Amino acid sequence: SDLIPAPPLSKVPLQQNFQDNQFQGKWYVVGLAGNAILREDKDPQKMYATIYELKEDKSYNVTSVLFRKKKCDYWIRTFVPGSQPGEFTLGNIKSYPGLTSYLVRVVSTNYNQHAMVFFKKVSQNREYFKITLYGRTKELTSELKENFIRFSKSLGLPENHIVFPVPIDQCIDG
Ligand SMILES: C[C@H]1OC(c2cccc(O)c2O)=N[C@@H]1C(=O)N(CCCNC(=O)c1cccc(O)c1O)CCCNC(=O)c1cccc(O)c1O
Ligand SMILES: [Cl-]
Ligand SMILES: [Fe+3]
């Protein structure tokens, strides 16, 4: 319970001209980074997928699907469009005990192969942040991964706080 501090928002770019319609669909967490994320060579992190669906009201219904304990687990929540396109906050924050704040900023994407998204939440008074490298496929070029590593580090994260989940087939195909 000691955390590297969330970076200031000025160190987190925002994708220009955000096309919310084009960001829809399944993305693969190809890379994971944040102040509560730890590399664990004993029990390495399995890849998971996060599906974004625009509703009529242009909120995202966001569903993450994870292979856990031999089953598929579904983490569902809503992203509400925020201050500027590419930026979001969390709907029904009341239903999450201890949660007082939640921010999403799409750092970059080209929509049809890769994306970088930054998350910042304050739960139980602790400030957590993470960056996810999203891939439309389960594998990305070494260039894009090093860019993920580089950017993670520009925000204070050491290497043991940067993770590339191992590709799996169960649950996240479909
Ligand atoms: C079944 C689990 O899978 C997920 C999950 C699955 C895919 C992507 C996510 O962002 C997820 O949170 N959440 C579930 C979960 O119970 N936890 C532990 C509970 C603490 N989380 C929360 O209180 C929470 C509340 C509202 C929205 C969220 O995204 C939240 O994480 C999650 C604890 C792990 N969280 C983090 O490492 C984290 C770190 C920084 C920022 C975040 O938004 C984070 O979720
Ligand atoms: Cl803790
Ligand atoms: Fe979360």
Image (cartoon, helix red, strand yellow):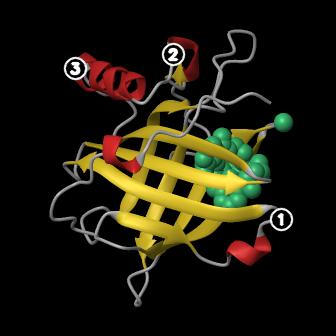
Q: Nearer the viewer, mark 2 or mark 3?
A: 2
Calculate the distance from the C-alpha at mark 2 to the C-alpha at mark 3: 19 Å
Looking at the rendering, which quadrant does residue 147 occupy? top left
Cα separation between marks 1 and 3: 39 Å
Q: Label 2 CB, ligand 1: below 8 Å?
A: no
The residue under the point 34% across, 38% down is 137
Q: Are marks 1 and 3 in contact (CB under 8 Å)?
A: no
Inter-mark Cα distance, 1 to 2: 29 Å
Q: Residues within 10 Å of mark 1 (few under 14, many from 20)?
A: few
From what the image shows, is residue 46 above or below residue 29?
Answer: above
Considering every residue shown, the one lying at the far top of the view is 41
Q: Which mark is residue 97?
A: 1
Check disc 2 and give the amino acid type: Pro
Q: Is residue 74 visible?
A: no
Q: From the viewer's perspective, is 123 left or right of 34?
A: right
Q: Is residue 34 left or right of residue 135?
A: right
Pointer 1 or 2: first along the chain: 1
State yes or no: Cβ of the residue under disc 3 lies below 8 Å from any atom of ligand 1. Answer: no
Asked if disc 1 is less than 8 Å from ligand 1, the answer is yes
User: Is any atom of residue 160 visible in this view?
Assistant: yes
In the foreground, 42 or 10: 10
Picture quarter containing residue 143? top left
Vertical order, 33 against 105 (above or below): above
- Counting from the top left corner in percent of width and height, residue 85 is at 28, 70
Disc 3 marks a residue whose amino acid type is Glu
User: What residue would you read off at disc 3?
Assistant: 143
Quarter the N terminus occupies:
top right
Q: Position of residue 164 (x, y in %)?
A: 49, 23
Going from the N terminus, do you reach mark 2 or mark 3 first?
3
Query: Contact, CB < 8 Å: mark 2 with mark 3?
Result: no
Residue picked out by circle 2: 158
In the displayed structure image, the side of residue 24 where residue 157 appears, left or right: right
